[PDB]
Amino acid sequence: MERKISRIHLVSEPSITHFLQVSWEKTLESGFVITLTDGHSAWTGTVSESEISQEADDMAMEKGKYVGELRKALLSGAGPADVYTFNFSKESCYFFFEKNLKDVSFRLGSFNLEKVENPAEVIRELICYCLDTTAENQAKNEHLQKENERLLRDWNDVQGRFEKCVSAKEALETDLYK
Amino acid sequence: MERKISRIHLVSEPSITHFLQVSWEKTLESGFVITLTDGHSAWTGTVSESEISQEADDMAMEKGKYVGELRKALLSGAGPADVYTFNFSKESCYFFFEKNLKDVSFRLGSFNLEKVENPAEVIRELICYCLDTTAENQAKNEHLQKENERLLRDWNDVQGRFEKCVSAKEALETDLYKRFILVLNEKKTKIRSLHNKLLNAAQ
Amino acid sequence: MERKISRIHLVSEPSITHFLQVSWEKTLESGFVITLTDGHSAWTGTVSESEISQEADDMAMEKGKYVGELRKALLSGAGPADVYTFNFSKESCYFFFEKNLKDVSFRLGSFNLEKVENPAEVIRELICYCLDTTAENQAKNEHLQKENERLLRDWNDVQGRFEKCVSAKEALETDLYK
Amino acid sequence: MERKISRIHLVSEPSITHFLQVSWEKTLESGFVITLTDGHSAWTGTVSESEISQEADDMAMEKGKYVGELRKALLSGAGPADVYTFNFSKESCYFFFEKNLKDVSFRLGSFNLEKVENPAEVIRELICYCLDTTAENQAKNEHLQKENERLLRDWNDVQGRFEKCVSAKEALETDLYKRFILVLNEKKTKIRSLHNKLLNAAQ
């Protein structure tokens, strides 16, 4: 399974940074689970692959394009120009996000999130994930430097073999064969 | 500032995974702030450079070795055989940790942690910090990657330019050589044209 | 425009008191200008609202919290416990301030200050500002006392009206109506 | 000690604003120290109680009125119609000021000012002094403010307690009154019960 964690700002609470954890199986369009967090409370919701496909229809868009918008808006895939906003009512339990073109905004999606009974468990899980992840990427990068390091020392060996070659030549002619 | 995050298990709470966030400026030896979390509440404390030197003396251990111990116990820098344990009284807010040696554990250090009034902000700050870290590292990957692909190309085409130089010089030289041979010959062809027609011109 | 003038002590010159003049338009986070003075020389620098927001990020803090720290440290908003220190190199032109928690200090900010070509003009301006200000606050307080004074004399009138009321009563019954 | 700061304009330097800092102990009449500044350099001098009395006599002016003039000219206590001028020779260090009367200015006083070796400290001291003043005054505001809010409440609830007293007494009294009326009646109801059944008991 795959996930993406990102930070957003709710239109109703601009002084605080909320977080988004979105996870899916093979593809985002195959359906995904979405969790919103403020670091203490947690709200989760599910979106089936049929609700997605259905929404793309209601919007006169090709499923691919819509999914694309979903990536940009929910998996932090937005471009420098793209501007997305997010809304959530901690009473309504209704979460909706919009795209803004020149200040003219249009609904892009919306779903209901239910309050998580055990938020600290979700959060602990999120941190473990990040921990494992940072560790993996640390390794990869560490292993990648060993490789670059090898290339350099591996190259330094060629230098030496070359010098020894020249000397063998600047010699052999002048000597051995006279 | 430097910052390190890791998971630990409290002796009194073996079922719930706790997190430790250590922040410091230059070396751990200069002091450092330490935060503990269960993802719901947060406790923070500070350990000064003095307290660190004091503790190290109380164990008759040279600072270096001690700072190293703090590094292993508190920054996940512990070896596979290293057994460190952590203790925290949520009523006392006294936190001490010990290194297990010869089946017996010895207190390696301690400190007090005030309860954090606003845990959420602390957790938020941690996730913010992780996001930056994940993003920062991913980029270093991609940069190291290209730097890697770069080196690999300079190699793949060095033995390319090299084989060409030789051919070049291998050519200029052969001319230079064939010439000299020609010179050696002319100096002998004139000798015959003469010595023969010279014994004709002279005698 | 708003400003705040305060006194600090540079780690490198503890025997002398330096001064800080910080000014901003609507908000501190909207960007501000900072001037350091020793009463003779002057060093000024600017901080845009984007450098601020940027710094809060690098520090894993919410813009609001960071700005808060800036107020406490640069506009003398520190609490009794808070301890901030300030550094400046009159060669490096580099100014940096740190917060100290139990003697363990952490960088909080830093910027470059350029030497002011006409320090006495800045200083004269600062004094005019203080002058105007002291005058305003003098007025306000002076006007506020006239008000308190009015209330007291205004109240003394009620006393008299009351006495005249009683007398009218202790009379009317005993007299007029007999 | 008392201290007053103000801006003035020197006749010889109409473009640069200068500052005057006057310090004294009880009354200006007891002597006082005066400092002049352009924010770069500083000149200081002292004017004794004697010199002040001497000058006042040299003008056949009663001390009181003269001290008042010094107050207006040197402590910003000058009226809207008052025109005072100031003169300073940075080469002589002689400073004299005059009051403009009937289109002609008359010297009101003078004194010498030695150049201050360390101007910065003087300026620093002034800003330090202003900081204290701004802080001290702001506090008096806040204190006067509360003292104000206080008085306003005692009023808003006095007409409250008052309306209640009346109701209280307005009640106790009505009982006290209704009783007496009852007494007056009983003294007449007995009269009838008797006089009628008494003319029956007697006759």
Image (cartoon, coloured by chain):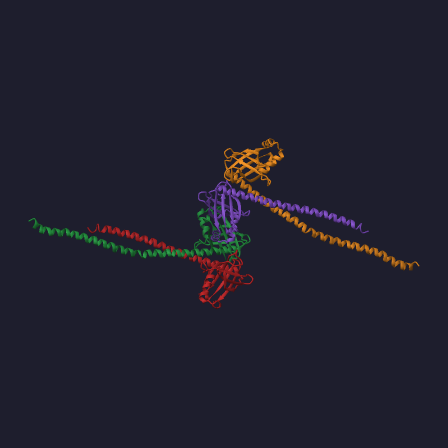
Chain colours: A red, B green, C purple, D orange
- Outermost residue, right side: D203
Image quadrant where one finds the N terminus of chain D: top right
Whole-percent x, y for residue B76 in the image: 45, 54
Q: Quadrant of the C terminus of chain D?
A: bottom right
View extreme (front): residue: D103
| Quarter of the view holding residue B160 | bottom left
Residue C38 in percent (x, y) is at 50, 41
Q: Tell which of B108 and A132 is nearer to you.
A: A132
One can see residue D162 in this view: yes
Q: Is residue C105 left or right of residue D188?
A: left
Count of numbered badges drawn on the protein: 0
Whether residue B51 is visible, yes or no, is no
- Residue at 44 percent of width and 66 percent of height: A64
Q: Position of residue C41 (x, y in %)?
A: 48, 41
**Where's residue B46, x and y in %?**
51, 49
Out of C10 and D103, give the one closest to the viewer: D103
Residue furthest to the left: B203
Question: In the image, is B31 to the left or to the right of D3?
Answer: left
Residue situated in front as seen by the camera: C97 or A35? C97
